[PDB]
Amino acid sequence: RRAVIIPARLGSTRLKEKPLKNLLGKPLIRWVVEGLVKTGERVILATDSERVKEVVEDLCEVFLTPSDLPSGSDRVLYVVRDLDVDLIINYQGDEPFVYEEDIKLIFRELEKGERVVTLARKDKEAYERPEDVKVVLDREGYALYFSRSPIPYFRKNDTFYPLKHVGIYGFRKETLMEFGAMPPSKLEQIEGLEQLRLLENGIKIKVLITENYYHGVDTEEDLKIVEEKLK
Amino acid sequence: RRAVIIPARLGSTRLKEKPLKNLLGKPLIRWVVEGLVKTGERVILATDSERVKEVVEDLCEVFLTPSDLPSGSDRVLYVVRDLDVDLIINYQGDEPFVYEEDIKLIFRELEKGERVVTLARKDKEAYERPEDVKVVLDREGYALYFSRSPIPYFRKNDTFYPLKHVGIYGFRKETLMEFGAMPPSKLEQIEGLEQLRLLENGIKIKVLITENYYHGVDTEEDLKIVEEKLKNL
Ligand SMILES: Nc1ccn([C@@H]2O[C@H](COP(=O)(O)OP(=O)(O)OP(=O)(O)O)[C@@H](O)[C@H]2O)c(=O)n1
Ligand SMILES: Nc1ccn([C@@H]2O[C@H](COP(=O)(O)OP(=O)(O)OP(=O)(O)O)[C@@H](O)[C@H]2O)c(=O)n1
Ligand SMILES: [Mg+2]
Ligand SMILES: [Mg+2]
Ligand SMILES: [Mg+2]
Ligand SMILES: [Mg+2]
C-alpha cells in the first residue's frame, strides 16, 4: 500500500526541458526512475509530456497531468486523489541520487506512526544560500522551523548544524490530502516554503539525518556538477 | 497566588552596575519596580547586591541570591523554588517600560492553562541585529523558533513579520522548575538563547503580540534610546 510519486514537468525554466537533459548519456528522469525502481517499490511518474513518459514507460507507471499545475506538490496531489494507497513518498524529478536505505528508512518511520517524515544532511555550503532550505530540530528530531535564512545563528560553534533540508517527503495519504485542503499559510507564503503549512497548522514533521549525497539539478552548473559526482 | 519576580544582579559587563545606572534622575531598577508596583501584583526583586536592595527596599520585597547564579531565570528559580506561588512572571531588571494590561494578559493566559507565555512586537529595525531576538509563530500563536538570525526570510515582504521577542515570561511554577532541571540544549547553546531549551524539549511557548514599546537596557546606546523615548511621551 505504498507508492513513490515523482512530479516531473517538461517546462523547466532555468534549464531547458530538464527531465530530458542528458546526464552521462542518459536523460535526468531516467536516472531518477532507475534508482527508484531498484528499491523494489511502486514508482509513479506524473508528467505533462509524452516525450518524458516515453523515456521511462518501460520501467514504471506514468500519468499525464495538466501542464499548468503550479507546483510539484499540486502535481502529486493531483494523482494521489485517484490512487488507492496508504503511504506516499514524494520524490523530486530532478534528484538523480537515490538510496534504497533512505527510502526504506522513510517508509519504516511512517509505519511507526509518523504522519510526515523528511530528510536533512549536515552541510555548511547551504547555510547562506537562500535557494537551500535550512532546518532546526527538537531533541526527538521533529522540525521546529525551516527557513531560507541562515539558521541557527552561530553565537557558539557546532559540528552537527547547519542542516540542509532535502525535499523528499513521506506522507500518510490522509495527511497529504489534509495539506492539499488547508489554505496557504502566512510563513509558507513569506518564505515560499510549502512545508511550513504543516508546521503552522501544528503537524509534526519527523526529520531523519542522512549522510548520503543529494543535490538537485536546477541549472546548467548543477548538471555539470552532478555529472562529475555520478562516477 | 501569583508574583512578579525581577532578577537584577549588580555585575553587568556591557554596562557597569546597570540596576543603579541613572535614568533621568532615577536608578534603572527603580523604574522597573515602580512600574510593576502599580500593577497591584506582588513584586519581588531578586538580587545579590545590598546597594541594589537599598534603592527599592521601600517599594517591594527583596530576596538575596548568590552572585554566581548563571542567568536571570536561574535567579528567579532560586527564589521561586521555595516560594508558595502558582504562577510567576520573570520581568527583566533592565526593562524600564511596564504596561499593566500586558501583565494581566500574561497571567490570564497562564490561567487558561498555558505553561509558558511571552511577548513579541512588530519591529522592522530588530531584523538584522543579532543582539535582538526574532520569533516566528504557528497559527495559534505558539513559537516555532526563536533566533538571532533574520527570520522569516522575506521571499516576499509582509504586514505582520518581522517580530522582536520581548524577554518577559510567565511560567507555571512547576514548569519553571522543570526548565531549571533540563540541561542546556543544543540550539540553546548555539544561539545563546535559553528559551530554546523549552522548544527543544517540546514545551509550548504561547506568544502574545503587544503594541506597547519595550526596549532592554544592555549598553550605553540602549540607555540613550530609552532616555529619548521617556522624554517623548
Ligand atoms: N509547476 C510545476 C513546478 C515544478 N514541478 C516539479 O517539481 C519539482 C521541483 O521543482 P523545480 O526543481 O523548481 O523544477 P522546475 O520548476 O521545472 O524548474 P524551474 O524552476 O527552473 O522552472 C520538479 O521535478 C518539477 O518538474 C511541477 O511538477 N510543476
Ligand atoms: N547571571 C545573571 C545574568 C543575568 N541576570 C539578570 O537577568 C537580566 C538579563 O540579563 P542581561 O540583560 O544580560 O544583564 P547582565 O547579564 O547582568 O549584563 P551583561 O550581559 O551586559 O553582562 C538582567 O536583569 C540581569 O540582572 C542575573 O540575574 N544573573
Ligand atoms: Mg521551479
Ligand atoms: Mg529543483
Ligand atoms: Mg547578560
Ligand atoms: Mg538585557
Image (tube, coloured by chain):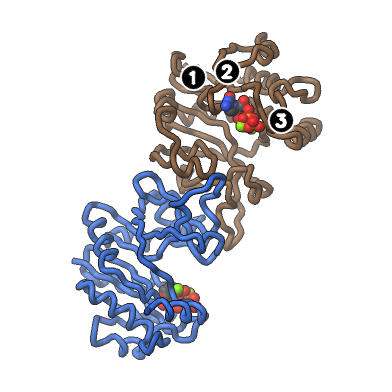
Chain colours: A blue, B brown
Say whether marks 2 and 1 touch (CB < 8 Å).
yes
Cβ of mark 3 under 8 Å from ligand 2: the answer is yes
The residue that mark 2 highlights is B46
Which comes before the other along the chain, label 3 or label 2? 3
- The image shows residue A169 at horizontal and vertical percentages of 34, 63
Vertical order, A88 against A32 (above or below):
above
Q: Position of residue A135 (x, y in %)?
A: 45, 55
Looking at the rendered image, the quarter that the N terminus of chain A falls into is bottom left
Ligand 1 shows up in the quarter that is: bottom left
- For disc 1, the marked residue is B78
Given contact means CB atoms under 8 Å apart, are the residues at marks 3 and 2 in contact?
Answer: no
Residue A87 appearing in the image: yes
Q: Position of residue A73 (x, y in %)?
A: 39, 69
- Marked residue chain, label 1: B
Q: Under 8 Å from ligand 2: the CB of mark 2?
A: yes
Q: Give the distance between the C-alpha atoms of the residues marked 2 and 1, in whole angstroms.
A: 9 Å
